[PDB]
Image 1: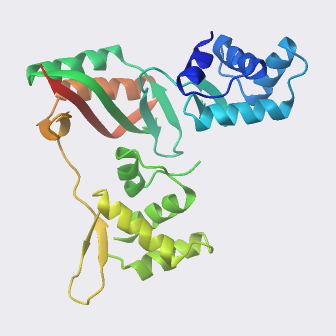
Image 2: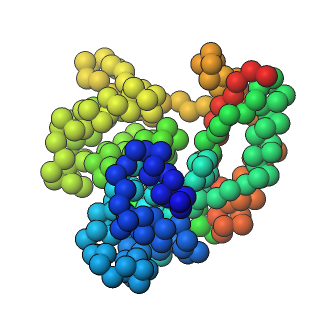
Length: 133
Length: 135
């Protein structure tokens, strides 16, 4: 059971082996594949998987908030597993590009702010807005 | 891509979806400085001829509901819009009671500038909301 497949099972989504292959490809990918790469890797596994099935499945994984479709800085639609906790966002105000980041350091300070006011931190939303240097 | 206008930034603060029409309307509002709906609509249609006055009205109303815009009658009877005040404090929210605890953290702000810097950016704004339950 791949992470993406596990996510599908939680959503009560219909799964078949072709959808499982696509889920596995997305889960095993070291990069953030575009649809062409998902297709190439999925058909390398089972050549019966059509390009249409790949588009349909990735879109479904999007619509069920299992995958995020994201521009990592190349203007391409690339796919990533939607994380267990939301990534923080740094927005380029000149282009509207979103840089997703994680900061265990900021998280530690967030916990301290919650603790000092007598709270357990249960979540956060952080947006940063920047202009390119 | 597009420039993130000052009003679009307020939308992003709220986690609102930036549809093309909302982006255009946010940009027009940002470039205006107390338009009525007709002025917003005329300016929005200069950018996207297919935007309707209904869409403009509904969008400015939504922005008002989310405290992005304020609406006032300055005497001429027209509802006129302006950017709502924004908070200087970040918020810790007790989710059980829906109560706000204001805080400022120069420390966390220094870290935010460091993140921006590391990615090749100067920080021009931020919003932080923390969600908590009592210990």
